[PDB]
Image: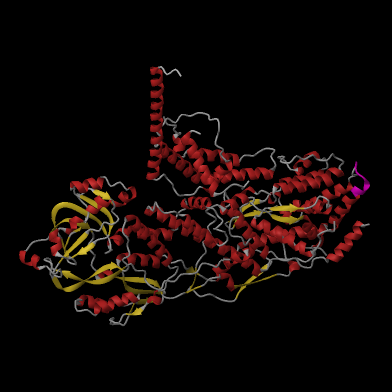
Amino acid sequence: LNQVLNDNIRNGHVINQLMEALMQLSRQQFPTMPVDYKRSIQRGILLLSNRLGQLVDLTRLLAYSYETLMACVTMNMQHVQTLTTEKLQLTSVTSLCMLIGNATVIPSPQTLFHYYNVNVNFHSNYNERINDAVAIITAANRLNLYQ
Amino acid sequence: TEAQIQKMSQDLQLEFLTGINSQAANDCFKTLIAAMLSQR
Amino acid sequence: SILKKLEDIKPEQAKAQTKLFRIFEPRQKPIYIANGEKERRNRIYWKLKKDTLPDGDYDVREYFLNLYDQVLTEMPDYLLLKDMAVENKNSRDAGKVVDSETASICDAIFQDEETEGAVARFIAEMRQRVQADRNVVNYPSILHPIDYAFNEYFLQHQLVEPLNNDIIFNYIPERIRNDVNYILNMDRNLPSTARYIRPNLLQDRLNLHDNFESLWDTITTSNYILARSVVPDLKELVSTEAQIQKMSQDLQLEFLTGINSQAANDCFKTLIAAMLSQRTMSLDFVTTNYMSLISGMWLLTVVPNDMFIRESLVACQLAIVNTIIYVAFGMQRMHYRNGDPQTPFQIAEQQIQNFQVANWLHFVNNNYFRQVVIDGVLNQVLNDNIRNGHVINQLMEALMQLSRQQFPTMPVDYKRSIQRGILLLSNRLGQLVDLTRLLAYSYETLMACVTMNMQHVQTLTTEKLQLTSVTSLCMLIGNATVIPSPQTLFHYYNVNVNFHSNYNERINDAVAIITAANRLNLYQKKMKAIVEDFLKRLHIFDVAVAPDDQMYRLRDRLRLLPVEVRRLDIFNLILMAMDQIERASDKIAQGVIIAYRDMQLERDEMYGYVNIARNLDGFQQINLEELMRTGSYAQITNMLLNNQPVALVGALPFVTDSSVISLIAILDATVFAQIVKLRKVDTLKPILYKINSDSNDFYLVANYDWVPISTTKVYKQVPVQFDFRNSMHMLTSNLTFTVYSDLLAFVSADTVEPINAVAFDNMRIMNEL
């Protein structure tokens, strides 16, 4: 089982719609808002809007690396809401969006093979320990080791 | 980082820019991709 | 600092060609008979002057982009062939040829046993012909067809144009010429051979005033500094001590802060320069200075309100209404909510019944600049009432109504203070009309010297203005008029022309390079360097601070522009002769054909027998560039293993081997196993056989009478011979001329008496006596 992304974000085309929305917001009137704060907000919007090409590149780079690393996962990618969550900093997201450059970085083949080997080893160990536990439990129940 | 921070400060005209740097950018990249991979 | 940077931009330097641009030269080579024996005489072939072509198609295209840059740098603006003229020693008439290398070629051909009498007589008759009446000269030259194409283009597309007194005078802006305050003069009748180069003054093509707010802010601040430098200094201001004592008597102290000539000149310059450069300006004031408020009323009357950031304008207007207007009419204080779509004046004109005050407020609300294209340049013209100073009458009528009001709900001292301040201005009423029309006239005259569109977009940063400085100007302006001097106007115009011309020339350079790289398909090249060079050459920006995204947006903006005619023509010549130039090299081949079949070596005079292929007809082609980009050696590995005949196409280096023993041993067929084993083709180096009488083993070919045969061939071109008569061309150019720059140096200008300086309405700017 794999958790797959929408093709529009895989190729990065939705960033164009995002920048359309941001441009509309930037030329929006903002009724009743104080003028200097309005200008700051809309120039902040333009800061991200004027990075259309860079953000398209960032999105499709992120999608490609996710696909390539997901090709090396062996267990089902079951999606559940976890008890404890990883904290993500919107400041860090801003830094990524405002500093992403022009160089494509992709996993090295050795890195992919290492990730795949680790996943395969963990998966096979998981199944083999299941087999050991089930065998022992069944043997105990068959030999009537009630204690 | 310095050039981008300077332009952001000029555009925002803060009569915000904290936490913006290459370390944070890489941390966010890794966090997003790894969280998607592990379904965390 | 900024002024130094913007004034140091020098006008474009004229480039005069000193030598003929050449890519080829004749080289004398041995030639062999059909059977491979030396012909006992030599032959001359065209060869590259600099055989530096690299291996790989991508590298070849990079080399040709670099060659395009070289030619663009070599392009001359004007050209005089007599400068590149040397005596042809073998001419019967002792004539002259049009280059040192031409003379060298003529000398070498003439002093040669193998040369034929026909060529000798041709050289003897080569000479130049001068037509003094038409001011033309024709010189013979010897150029390979491609070189001749380039040099003929240079000769036919020079940038110089005729010059004379009428052109020099017309170079001045029309509005200065049409201005009766300036008398222009000349003391030189330029000849009929004078030349000049017109600046490139196309209006901004990148539209930097749209979505490039940081770059636009830099441009605007540079223009603002320049405008401040050129705005004249006020003269004969009323003595500050006298004015202070007089207004102390008027106010009966028992308002004056910031009154002085320094602040008066500061305010005058700041206003005019801010309007010229379209810099937004903020207003700095303290609500406790009612005189500052009154002077702000005058300022908002005179200068259109779009020149202030909304918050400063709104603060000033709110202070004005709540301290003067509503108070005088006994109206409740305006609770003005920040961010309201309407300004305090816009609200007050609706709430106020008095016609004078309402009319003045309405004028202030709906007063705008007018965008007008004047003499091909967009200008922000003021209202004619402001230009002739009539708005001051409206302002004073409003102020008089306010001072007449009864000020209900406030103690008597409040009304007393308000009317004392209004009196301070009313005493200066006439001086206010004079100051208004003086400001308008100086603005118009300095705006006549602007060459780039006066775009009106609020800037990131603002210029601070003190209402105390406005008050000082209003309280200290005297009777003397100040008109921009003709020298200052010419200097301002020349600075603007230089900046505009540099801007357009760098735009053209960047566009040409970008379009050429796209045409040559340099898909691994990043143009951030090109944009960085463009911005650095603009001389006023901080490229180190400009981030990458802005530079790539600039590249996108540049990509849509058309290419200059001359640069586009140069690129077209380069790209059409590109194949010939690449294939004339002796350092690379165009590919290798592996046939696995016996193919007789082709016989060429300058090689003997050679395994040359002129065309890849009948062979499946593999693109080595694509192979190296992709890295998948599956197709080529399979073909090499299965001995399937193929043609590996690309720019390859080759090893020239002249051993008949090697040819018999079939060494040329043993150079491809490396592709299969190492799985790389960047080291591929096919063997070009060269069998002839100088091969040290040619007795095998001579005695056994066999045509040599090889199983592989090198895709190459045979060099083209050098035909002297066919290569002689007569280059034509002007005999002589002198190229002038800085046209306004020939014009001497002076002003009329300042007392008699006349405004647009034919009346004196300042009339107070």
Q: In the rendering, at what x and y percent does residue A36 appear?
A: 68, 45
Position of residue C744 relative to residue A29, above or below, is below
Which of the 4 image quadrants contains residue C742? bottom right
- Classify the position of the N terminus of chain C by image quarter: bottom right
- Could you say which is closer to the camera, residue C274 or residue A99? A99
Residue segment shown in magenta: C408-415
- Could you say which is closer to the camera, residue C305 or residue A80? A80
Q: In the rendering, at what x and y percent does residue C642 appear?
A: 18, 46
**Is residue C56 visible in this depiction of the protein?**
yes
Which of the 4 image quadrants contains residue C46? bottom left
Q: In the rendering, at what x and y percent does residue A130 appear?
A: 41, 27
Number of marks drawn: 0
Using residue C681 as the reference point, say whether residue C707 is left or right of it. Answer: left
- Residue in the image at 32% along x and 62% along y: C53
- Residue in the image at 68% along x and 57% along y: C274
Which of the 4 image quadrants contains residue C39? bottom left
Using residue C266 as the reference point, say whether residue C77 is left or right of it. Answer: left
- Classify the position of the C terminus of chain C by image quarter: bottom right
- Could you say which is closer to the camera, residue C248 or residue C369? C248
- Could you say which is closer to the camera, residue C685 or residue C523? C685
Q: In the rendering, at what x and y percent does residue C197 appear?
A: 50, 67
- Residue in the image at 52% along x and 44% along y: B27
Q: Is residue C409 shown in magenta?
A: yes
Position of residue C725 relative to residue C397, above or below, is below
**Is residue C764 visible in this depiction of the protein?**
no
